[PDB]
Length: 143
Length: 71
Image 1 (cartoon, rainbow over the protein chains, first blue to last red):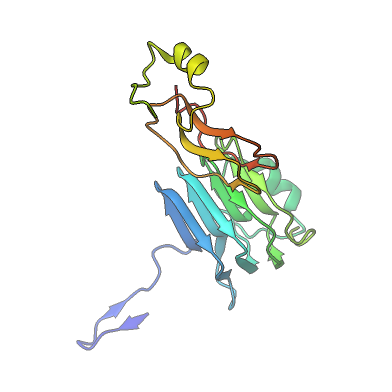
Image 2: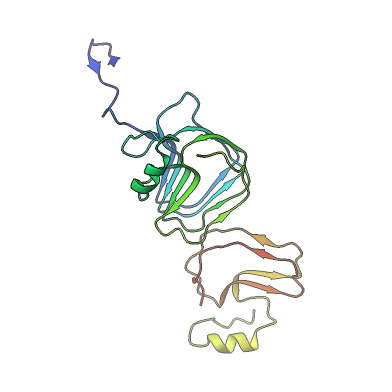
């Protein structure tokens, strides 16, 4: 609860089920993400590390990706014990991976190093993403 | 290269008479080793093709850009 200089109090949260991500991209074209990092150090509640929706040509060159704490859009924690249930009930949900890609033309990722991914998958593709190309990143890091 | 307009109407004629011309695409590649393009977004291409390759360009590699934008 934030206390102002006029001795007011403001609730930081909007709802008790709040989730976020590191970067959100919607309605863009010809986007290049060269190098850099996207990481969840400190265990925030994330649906993904990067969410990409309704873009033409999003390209990732060697970006460092690590340390996600997985949640669905609702706020449900994605753990090993319920992983199968998630795959049935949240297939159309925009969450569940380190990189979520929805309705994106010309998506491309090369081979960066990825580790400590505590969510269902490393890349999720949905909603008519139809000419993607996936390079060889570190395997077997997700759930 | 002459100065002839490339439209839909005459498109077939062009492909017959200007095969060896260095023109007719968004990107024209001639005698180039090691050419490479990844997948950018391309639109509004009022010419015969998106990429033309010619004159011994022999190890090119084409990623998936936006399909169906040329004539």
